[PDB]
């Protein structure tokens, strides 16, 4: 449900082919929040339960609302936590294709982590999805040091955080349909583009 630790719990001897690391929004529960479970269900349908590991960013990432105001849109401790997860994936399963995503503060977290990542690991992330991306305007719809063709941003009209503000309006809470369809569609397509099928 809202908590998935497939990478942490996973057996190195039987690595999944695909590893998905997702960061939840502010004040959300577990380590997947409101959108992560929907994406996970569809990924499992496409790759099979044993074909993909779903890993939420928990630990030091408290998803504290106030941290949206920090320089990178999240805390240093949260960035360290997500970086460590990408590092764990790379060490535990060097041949797995990675995919990532985040919502709201988690989208800023995903962008900051990917920017700081060792390039050899960053280059293994086949696709990244960002919902209600709080640094959308500041970063011009991109994740620094990461290609545009591997990035998909879902920013609703009227979602003020996509337009340089930190005000939470109704459109910021309307990403359900995207998480159920286009987001997993994009991730599956990007994985198949490099892995074949």
Image (cartoon, rainbow, N blue to C red):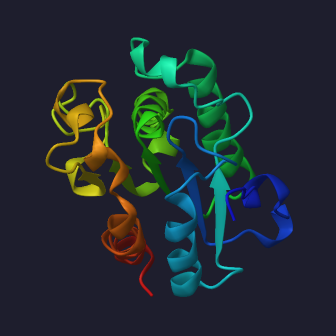
Q: Nearer the viewer, residue 51 or 59?
A: 59
The answer to whether residue 34 is seen in the rendering is: yes
56 lies left or right of 124: right
Residue 17: image location, x then y, percent: 62, 72
Where is residue 166, by image quadrant? top left
Residue at 67% over, 51% down: 89
1 lies left or right of 38: right
Residue at 44% over, 36% down: 114
Residue 186: image location, x then y, percent: 32, 69
The answer to whether residue 98 is seen in the rendering is: no
Residue 197, compared with residue 175, is above or below; it is: below
Residue 114, compared with residue 5, is above or below; it is: above
Residue at 22% over, 56% down: 149
122 lies left or right of 189: right
Where is residue 2, by image quadrant? bottom right
**The N terminus - image quarter:** bottom right
Residue 122, compared with residue 35, is above or below; it is: above
């Amino acid at each position: 449900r809202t908590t998935r630790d497939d990478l942490i719990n996973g057996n190195s001897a039987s690595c999944a082919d695909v590893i998905f690391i997702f960061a939840r929004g502010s004040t959300e529960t577990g380590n997947l929040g409101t959108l992560g479970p929907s994406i996970a269900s569809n990924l499992e349908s496409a790759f099979g339960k044993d074909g993909v590991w779903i890993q939420g960013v928990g630990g030091a990432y408290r998803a504290t609302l106030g941290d949206n105001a920090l320089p990178r849109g999240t805390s240093s401790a949260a960035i360290r936590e997500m970086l460590g997860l990408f590092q764990q994936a790379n060490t535990k399963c060097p041949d797995a294709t990675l995919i990532a995503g985040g919502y709201s503060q988690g989208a800023a977290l995903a962008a900051a982590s990917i920017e700081d990542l060792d390039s050899a690991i960053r280059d293994k992330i086949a696709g990244t999805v960002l919902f209600g991306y709080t640094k959308n305007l500041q970063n011009r719809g991109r994740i620094p040091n990461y290609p545009a063709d591997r990035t998909k941003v879902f920013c609703n009209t009227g979602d003020l955080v996509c337009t340089g503000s930190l005000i939470v309006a109704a459109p910021h809470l309307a990403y359900g349909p995207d998480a159920r369809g286009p987001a997993p569609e994009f991730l599956i397509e990007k994985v198949r583009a490099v892995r074949g099928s």
